Amino acid sequence: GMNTLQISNVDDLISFYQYADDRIPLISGHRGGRGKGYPENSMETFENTLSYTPATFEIDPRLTKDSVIVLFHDDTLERTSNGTGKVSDYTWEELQNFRLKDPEGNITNYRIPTLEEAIRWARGKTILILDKKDVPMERTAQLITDMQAEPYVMITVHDGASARFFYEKNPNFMFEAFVKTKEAVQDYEDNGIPWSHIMAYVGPKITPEVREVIDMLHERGVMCMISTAPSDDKLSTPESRAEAYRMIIRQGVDIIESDRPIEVAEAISSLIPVSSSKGKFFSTL
Amino acid sequence: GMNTLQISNVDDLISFYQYADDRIPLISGHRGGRGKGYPENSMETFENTLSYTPATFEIDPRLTKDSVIVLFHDDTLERTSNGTGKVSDYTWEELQNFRLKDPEGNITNYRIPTLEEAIRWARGKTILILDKKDVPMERTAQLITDMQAEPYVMITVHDGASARFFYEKNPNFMFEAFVKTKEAVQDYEDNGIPWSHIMAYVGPKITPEVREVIDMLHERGVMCMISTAPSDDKLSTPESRAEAYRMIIRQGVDIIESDRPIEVAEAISSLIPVSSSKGKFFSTL
Ligand code: NA
């Protein structure tokens, strides 16, 4: 039994991400989310997270020796698998011999997944958000376009010029855009990226400056995301982490990206409104 | 002793990189160059390389836990050191306890260097070229500027927008710019970046399209570099590699960036002009 998002096409995706004052706080699993028995960038972890909360998943596509795109964050295999060396030293088939490790170092029986497997699974359940490692931008553009996956596979962009590369190739793409400053807001505008095609990553922490950016972005219809992965996820107790996740929502932030999405869900459950224009986008499978 | 480049100020650096038909073919050590007993991104490898050839060094700055800039390519420690985990997990004091591995996996008694130490050492000897890992652009701009290191520390930029960010901060910066297509040529012009401040990285291989871009760039006074690191450096024998390096220069390329810069030097020494407008920039220490 899983929580799902109900986004049938690009118009639904744009709507989902149009800021509204009655919006539902959103959760995104950093590198898929992780936990005891649940490695980063694993199909199993995505599925586990949806059993507790609706979420999107930010993932790490990178290349094997035979140019297969797999999900795996690091430049070396040791932290989140029982392998050694670079992902790009091994074919996909060879990579299947390794097993993923959870954050405690326990070796699971889960394998490195392909991006294709994740995309096929995500359709009708969630939205994936692609970070950039070593897959060429043109390849990423073509894979999403060829697969008609625009309604459920978003692209992370660090500035307006990268956004424009993608947007000019396919104007139905949706972006997670880095927007940490007033100058960043101007950058996207100068590059002609529609705000309707933007959800904004505003950084790892809230400051008065970042609050001003969030107000600017809300005026433009843009939802804003804090990533707690480097910051509040690292607090020593679940109780301190829970307080921190609630404080982020109380400050007006729309989306929390976290390595601990289930904890985020439990902490903010009491903040989820009963009535919302966004209620229609949520269901269960 | 050592081969040195004799560059006294930013005007000398600009003139060094002004394309001329009688140029001296140049060599750049990718990730600093490497070899048996000589790890990537190591002071010792830079010094060894200069004993055999003049060269520049392309290096990988990244952040420690306490925001010190060190040189280390991978996001995790296992391939080129005896460390485990991420460079950013450790403070500089902790990282100094680890030791570097050469490409065959042999542990040396060499440490992960700071960018500062490298900059200190490079002054009067060579030019360092900074790749982009996780040091933000603002921080890179500051450190070069604060150190008055513009004549000997270049910044790699992937497009005109990145170049513009830097150039607006300090119009004395010199760039290694990615310029792989006619569209990329136009990008730098549209962003107002003077060609006098650009050396061009044109990719890992020569094709007719790339030869056309090299022609265009030569017309604009821009010297062009091929990286052999993913390509010709991987050929199986030193003889095949040497033929490959000569062919690159025969095809009109100005600069070879390589993991094997001493081999490049030995291969192309027979192609170095005996009289050149660029002779003045080379000396010995
Ligand atoms: Na320091």
Image: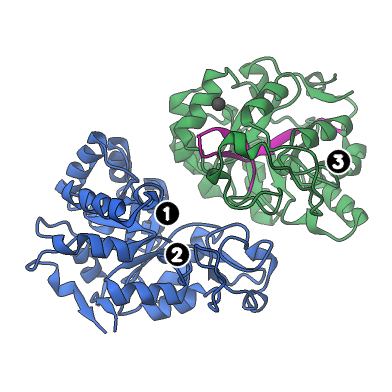
Chain colours: A blue, B green
User: Mark 2 — residue?
Assistant: A141
Residue at position x 38%, y 50% in the image: A236
Report the magenta residues as a range: B53-73
Between residue B75 and residue A185, name the one nearer to us.
Answer: B75
Residue tagged 3: B262
Q: Secondary structure at mark 3?
A: helix
Q: Is residue A21 left or right of residue B43?
A: left
At which x and y percent is residue A61? Answer: 51, 65
- Residue A153 percent location from the top left of the image: 37, 68
Picture disc at residue A165: 1
For image coordinates 62% across by 26% down, the residue present is: B116
Q: What's the residue type where badge 3 is placed? A: Ile
Can you tell me whether the CB of the residue at mark 2 lies under 8 Å from the nearest atom of ligand 1?
no
Q: Quadrant of the N terminus of chain B?
A: top right
Inspect the image, locate mark 2, and give the three-letter code of the amino acid beneath it: Ala
Label 2 residue SS = helix
The structure residue drawn at horizontal position 71% and vertical position 48%, both measured from the top left corner, is B81
Instruction: Kindly report which numbered mark, 2 or 3, lies closer to the viewer in this rendering.
Output: 3
Amino acid on which disc 1 is placed: Phe
Answer yes or no: are tags 3 and 1 on the same subunit: no
Marks 2 and 3, how far apart in space? 39 Å
Could you say whether the residue bearing mark 1 is in a helix, strand or loop? helix
- Whether discs 2 and 3 lie on one chain: the answer is no
